[PDB]
Structure formats: C-alpha cells, structure tokens
Amino acid sequence: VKIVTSQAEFDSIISQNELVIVDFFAEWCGPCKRIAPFYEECSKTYTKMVFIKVDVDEVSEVTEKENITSMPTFKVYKNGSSVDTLLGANDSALKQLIEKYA
Amino acid sequence: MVKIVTSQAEFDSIISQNELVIVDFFAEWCGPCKRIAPFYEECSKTYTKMVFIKVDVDEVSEVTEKENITSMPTFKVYKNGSSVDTLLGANDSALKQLIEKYA
Image 1 (cartoon, rainbow over the protein chains, first blue to last red):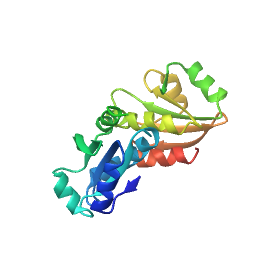
Image 2: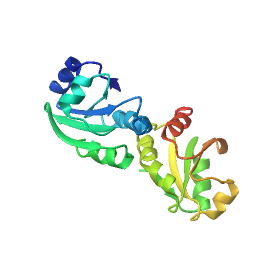
Image 3: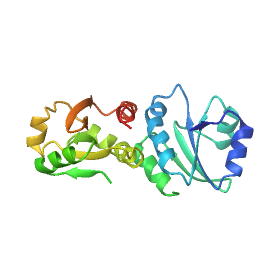
C-alpha cells in the first residue's frame, strides 16, 4: 500500500484515478496501527480502487487542507473530489465504506 | 464466503478432503471473535490456497473438546488432516502472519 510522502504526490494520485481511498494514519496512534493489516488486505481484493496511506504529520500540508480531526480517518475520492469520509478504526465499518464504492 | 461447520462429521470431512484448512473457533458470546470476523472473511477471499471454515465452540462441543480449545478465539491450521499450527487471541497482525505462513 503506497504511503504518500508529499502534497504533489497526493494531488497527482487523486486527480488521475477515478476511485481513491486514503487512510490518514500516524505512528503515534494505536488504533491506526491496529487496522493497518485489514486495510492492506482490502487493497488486495478491492482492485477497482486505489489504496493509499498518508502520515498526518509527514504531510501536514495535506492534513490541514483535507481538514482531519480524529485518527484514523479514511476519505474516499471520486474523480478528484472528497465523497465519503469515515472516522475511527473499526473493521466492519471500513469494509462497509469500501464496498460502497467497489 | 466462509463455511460455518455445524457437525463433527462435516468438520472431519473438510479436514480430510482438503490439503490446507484453517479453522476459526468462535462463539456468539465472545466479543473478540466478532471483532476479528470481517478480517478472517477478507483473508479467505485472497489467500485462496487454503480453505477457511468457522466452528462455533458450543454448537460443535464434540469438536471443541477433541481439538482441546481453551481460549477464545482460537485459530488452528491443518495440513493433510493433522493439526500443525495454532494461534490464540484476536489479533489481525498475528492472524495474517499465521495465514501467510501457509499461503
């Protein structure tokens, strides 16, 4: 699962893929680490969607622009725009979000 | 997509008609078991080399007593009809590791 290291790379991936999900994680956040393996797993089966990760401190610029309050946050983008957004680390909840779009 | 096994005969059959079987010993009274269910179902979709089954410890008492299941949940893997590895607890990272060890 691609970890995005810059604004440019974020803006680029989101703009030239019709379906992208982004997992806003951080190494200081336990729940994020908990759900990572499940996220990795889904990215394997739900091939209609591009899976990326963004470390909220690593790319501050993107977190402040995407307005992230709690941790983790999963946002999906369709055609370059924010469409759905889920807060927290629950497996079934995240499954339900992904299936909504693939 | 993950068979719930409802009898010892069926348990025995699957274990013996299949090269690799992983089994998730769950129960409806066990919170942890319910949490890890979606990950297990997901894994079954991708790690196709291996047959995933669930067994409810109380529904199939005879099996849980024979397989000597103490903690909940328990995942066992079987290669060629014999118990080969067993993981206790509901940890996504750990369960992945166990499955990856065989597919």
